[PDB]
Image 1 (cartoon, rainbow over the protein chains, first blue to last red):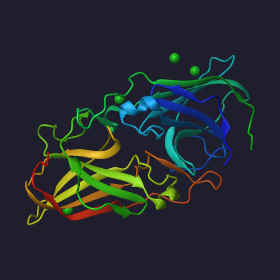
Image 2: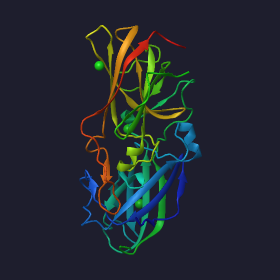
Image 3: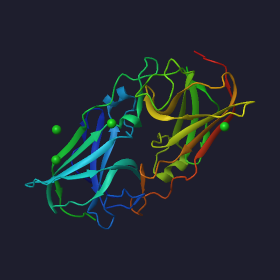
Image 4: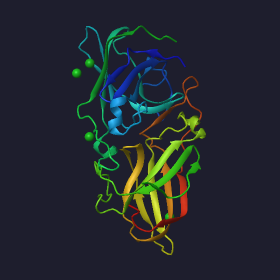
Length: 158
Length: 157
Ligand SMILES: [Cl-]
Ligand SMILES: [Cl-]
Ligand SMILES: [Cl-]
Ligand SMILES: [Cl-]
């Protein structure tokens, strides 16, 4: 299926982050707050894999990084309104990603698109820290940010 | 030094391995697992997608996250069963479902059963549209990987 870029891929902390968008999808179970395939404008996806700095956390470099909490903020140029979109983990035909069906609430135009990526919640993931089997890295405390200041929403490309 | 619980199993879309080795220190320390000092060992359930596998959108060999894994231990000659809830974590060699464990009934031969449940309803999704989506669906009842003659003789380290 056709994917369109949001902007240039970013390397932030131990993460390589890509952003793409494409036609709205039908998800099962549907994230309850996300617009249906009919009501959405598009599906946005954050593709997140460990980079070389991720090795210190125990991830294989290039592997998908699960259990993260990803939120996107969309803000049309010249507007003070900011849309907050919670992404959810899911599999598509091409593997796991974090994503959401969305609506660009202020219509066609240029938007600032920001992904804020939080490490796993305290009780959802652990690291081995003993010298023998452990890792020397640790999860980031402040969310990591990947952003594009001039994304053009020019309507469906499908 | 890692030791197998038994031979790897292929159950549905999962390639499941079980190994044990010395206790580890985890941060945060999960649920009610014993500390590195209190534990007998660390047991890991290594779960990766097999060819069947691709039907859910995974790539062969990929770690399968968001699963809920529990182990049941029963010493031969005993009616008692100990439940071990595994937690997701990274070690220096990558992601695993693991747990520090203290064998309540001590030394002996055990029946070891891993029950693997698909992600919770609100924890994961599949694209199901024709265009972007997948044909497979998660399993309802937990998948089982079992070894009947696991020998616990004490630390091998
Ligand atoms: Cl913003
Ligand atoms: Cl937290
Ligand atoms: Cl910032
Ligand atoms: Cl049992």
